[PDB]
Image: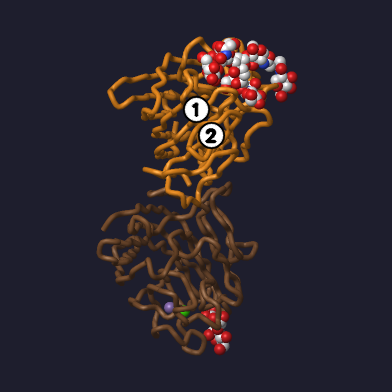
Chain colours: A brown, B orange
């Protein structure tokens, strides 16, 4: 289970409970979601994701209960260029989820090209930190960097303008209150700059009772490192 | 991960994070470690165990840290016989642990006959609630029902007299403080009757850095049900 929590203050190399997909790997006590060359620089055309191995019981039909959850994490993006792409996302999906074919670049390794904007064809909730919005390839993005809440589509149901800071860690807190059904996102840089965005969502109609949680990131022709530095998570089934 | 925690107030039939071994299965929101017929009656010659799927980081060689953990659980034993057997145990072992060949009866599904008392051929720490002590078969046991702390051997490093109460739930709290290296056990029946037993053990010299936790139970010629009713576990790495 009714409750589950875990915390990674750092990411040592001897991991046992993480499912690594794509190019994701541990380097310097942090998770490098996207590939990097020998000297630690970001490269183009790369996708990577990680999921915690234990499944989370998001909701239970028999007891009519729904879980609340809180995911706290920090990441940093770095790039030689100034148009780093494509972004990192915290997501929740069915337990057997895998990188969809052709989900690189602006699809963040979460959606397939042909069904990226088809809500009845996906089962995923993600909080994206999108740094690339060129209208030729990312036709669905607002015209500026942003934090978005994605519900079964790459076209966010709600966004807030965000600023990308090269090499600076962003502290994020994602919370889902089953009582109000609000998914709240609070992100802050160390100097106090704060960004907030929320949306009301009934998780029971979007995801199965048991899911897995993790992160995804990608770089198409434009690139940047997507470094996940720490992550804590907790969920508890509740009667509302 | 550095910290992991989970709680099972009850055990619904739909489980995803438990590894079932032997005859263990879910029945009536509880785990029946040993096999029962269609009427829910215990039968002879049965062994079963469960383990949480996520591995627990018990200690870390590189940082000189050892986990502080707590396992709270409750179980009940029932049998029409005057000498129900054989007992249930909470245990900690390497991740790939499986039921040893020929470990039934008094071996509780934790040790192989040929090496049951060879502390050098085993890697396990368990807290047993032993109800069968026939001196002609369980030669290693004291002559009475008991709670025991097992360290790489079926011959407990320590035991205390315990009363078996048919059909009554026993609540148990097992904790380990890495500072004092004390493994404490406190068990209580609903009327306030209490049993305590403690032992100093350096887990680092007994178990690998990553382990799995769970329960094991068995019945030889004599039988009884071994029902795990609830279980919550928490673990956190600390400096020592
Ligand atoms: C290798 C070797 O040398 N072996 C034997 C010893 O085993 C033997 O001792 C006897 O062993 C019996 C079998 O042991 C198995 O079961 C027990 C209990 O579950 C386990 O603890 C053992 O580890 C072992 O378990 C596993 O069994 C499976 C399957 O059989 C096997 O595959 C596994 O390999 C095995 N595991 C291992 C590690 O070996 C044991 O049952 C005997 O215990 C009885 O007898 C002693 C005295 O001799 C007594 O103190 C006990 O309480 C028990 O008493 C009997 O209890 C039953 C149940 O109540 C009675 O039957 C009931 O009686 C009432 C009347 O009152 C009615 O009639 C009911 O209908 C009826 O059910 C029965 O009457 C009791 N019998 C007696 C004599 O009192 C014992 O320890 C020794 C000596 O025989 O020889 C070898 O060393
Ligand atoms: O990684 C950024 C982006 O790269 C790819 O699209 C390209 C960009 O829009 C830009 O470089 O212009 C190119 C030419 O029009 C275009 O290919 C894709 O991989 C895209 O998904 C990704 O977001
Ligand atoms: C103890 O177990 C080890 C490893 O299995 C074995 O090599 C050794 O012979 C055993 N010692 C005794 C005294 O049985
Ligand atoms: Ca984009
Ligand atoms: Ca015994
Ligand atoms: Mn976007
Ligand atoms: Mn014993």
Q: Can see residue A18?
A: yes
> Quick one: label 1, few (<14), some, or many (20+) residues within 10 Å?
many
Q: Mark 1 lies on which chain?
A: B
Q: Nearer the viewer, residue A96 or A110?
A: A96
Q: Do the residues labelled 2 and 1 touch (CB within 8 Å)?
A: yes
Name the residue that disc number 2 marks.
B34
The number of discs equals: 2
Q: In the image, what residue occupies the spot 28% across and 23% down? A: B191
Q: Position of residue B198 (x, y in %)?
A: 42, 19
Q: Position of residue B103 (x, y in %)?
A: 64, 27
Q: In the image, what residue occupies the spot 34% across and 25% down? A: B188
Q: Where is residue A133 in the image (x, y as percent from the top left)?
A: 45, 82
Q: Is mark 1 on a helix, strand or loop?
A: loop
> Quick one: label 2, few (<14), some, or many (20+) residues within 10 Å?
many
Q: Which chain carries label 2?
A: B
Q: Position of residue A8 (x, y in %)?
A: 45, 50
Name the residue that disc number 1 marks.
B224
**A5 lies above or below B145:** below
Q: Which of A53 and B28 is in front in this view?
A: B28
Q: Can see residue B138?
A: no
**A206 lies above or below B213:** below
């Amino acid at each position: 289970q009714d409750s589950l929590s875990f915390g990674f203050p750092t990411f040592p190399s001897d991991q046992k409970n993480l499912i690594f997909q794509g190019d994701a790997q541990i380097k310097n006590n942090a998770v490098q979601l996207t590939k990097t060359d020998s000297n630690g620089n970001p490269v183009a055309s790369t996708v990577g994701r990680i999921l915690f191995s234990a499944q989370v019981h998001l909701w239970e039909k028999s007891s009519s209960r729904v879980a609340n959850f809180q995911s706290q994490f920090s990441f940093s993006l770095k790039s030689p260029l100034s148009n780093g792409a494509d972004g990192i996302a915290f997501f929740i999906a069915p337990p057997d989820t895998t990188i969809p074919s052709g989900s690189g670049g602006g699809l963040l390794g979460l959606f397939a090209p042909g069904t990226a904007q088809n809500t009845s064809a996906n089962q995923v909730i993600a909080v994206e930190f999108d740094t690339f919005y060129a209208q030729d390839s990312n036709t669905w993005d607002p015209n500026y960097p942003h934090i978005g809440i994605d519900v079964n589509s790459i076209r966010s149901v709600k966004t807030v303008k965000w600023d990308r800071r090269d090499g600076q860690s962003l502290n994020v807190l994602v919370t889902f209150n089953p009582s109000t059904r609000n998914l709240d996102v609070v992100a802050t840089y160390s100097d106090g700059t704060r960004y907030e965005v929320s949306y009301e969502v009934d998780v029971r109609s979007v995801l199965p009772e048991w899911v897995r949680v993790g992160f995804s990131a990608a770089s198409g022709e434009q690139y940047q490192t997507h470094t996940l530095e720490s992550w804590s998570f907790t969920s508890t089934l509740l009667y509302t």
